[PDB]
Image (cartoon, rainbow, N blue to C red; front, side):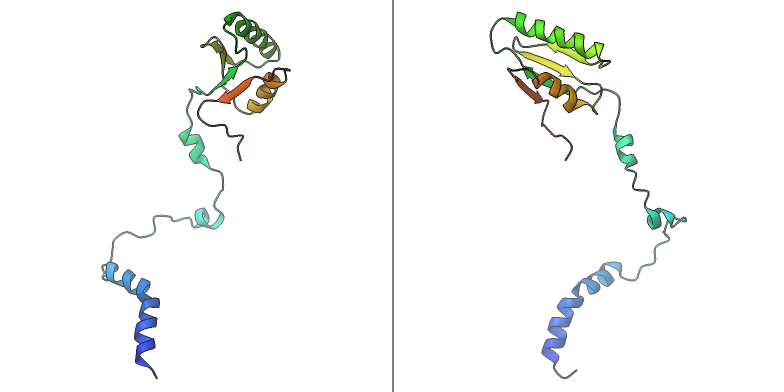
Length: 141
């Protein structure tokens, strides 16, 4: 306590957060104790994001908009998409495929793991074609 100015000013500005806590607390004791009896929850923290399982539900309407032809004749898209419908199902890849938009073949996946795998199979053709995802195109990270 050799200098008032620095102490009160700077130290209060530093302790401001602590004083704020004390001020909003006002020393009122709540009946609410730590509800977690097994500290092991915060001790270990399982890491398993169960939230995803709680957030997920059946009804994966995620499709890939595959602009195959680019030519008015819907035939081309139907032919190639039915060929894919063959090969995929023959490869045990049971997926949903519809032709809405003469050029746009939509592949709706009930799965996800092999999303880029089937996508690869699609773009594996010389033409490549436009294969977009409903919404955004995210591989994962």
